[PDB]
Length: 187
Length: 208
Length: 54
Image (tube, rainbow over all chains, first blue to last red; front, side, top):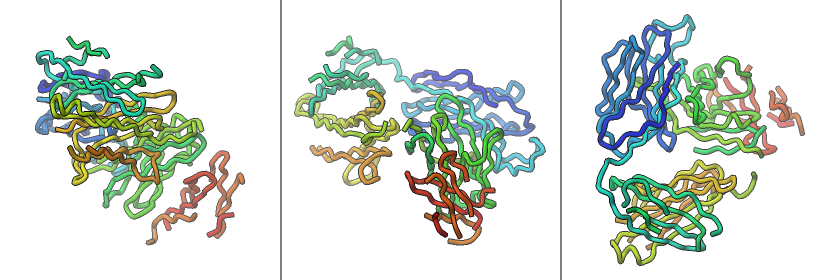
């Protein structure tokens, strides 16, 4: 069993975020895997930390494994923008031959037990407020409002859809409001 | 990446696990709010299906269409069966996971659920203001929400960094838009959706 | 296709002659023969560990 009590944590870019995952086990030797599920739902392996190994490290990723406390919390240091995902702490025993139940399974039949995951939001770093430029694009009875605005707090008739706010690669925010209409409030 | 099938039907999950010396292929279901959980694993050498305890036989089947190929088959689909499915095989440092396909089980709405493309060619406004415009393509009333909108060039298969808005349910289908800001050229917008024209994924031209 | 493999061979009950019958209602056909419905009113027999539709 894996217990990730806290989900949807938020941290800025270039800081370090520690994802706290616990586990319940009856295995003498085991491994804990840290995966990240991308928005494309492509579960990407990040780090492996054995029960009888030193605290694992994979460049940016590190693990603070506490065998007695069963705290194998991951740490990501110097986050960049493309770090937001659903981070899964998974207890498995792949390369383990002694210390599990008396089943004749050859560890290739062993399941990787997952925790419910923690979504990580990589907010952009604090920076001076920026005035956004607005383009009202219309093509075929449809209106799209394009807004360089910090922070994400911005406000913008057959139907009007929820505006989408995204973190631009410029280390700021960009939003688009879609509506079948056919202003600016950021400072 | 998306498989939409009615209730009381059969759904197939194929995946890009290119593992050759695989001996067991596990099928994990992530139901988006719970943990990814194994439904079964397929003994490749003996070709057997080991279901998890408390299940019933015939709910899940592992098919071998080719040599090193597997497909999870679900009979008498129900809505609880919806989720994301992965084929996972243990690797030396980790457990390799397939790209994962979303199986959404509908009640039966049945209409043209292809993503309807609306195209927003920028005016001369951005070229006048900061000589850098944006091309935005939206897709209305598609089912399921599982879509992949990304932009490439004519001369390359490079996934250009393109801003992608969220997906929003209209009434029961979904709408999703994506814009790319040119730093001009024919930047194409590829839309990966299950329901498209002639089976192949959708594609939109964006001329200057 | 080699041996030790799977073979794909393309009304309430659909019977297979050379074996089994598939009930579409409760969707019921161990593991040697399986019936898969890739489409609506389309059935394919799958044989693991290596024919007429009736």
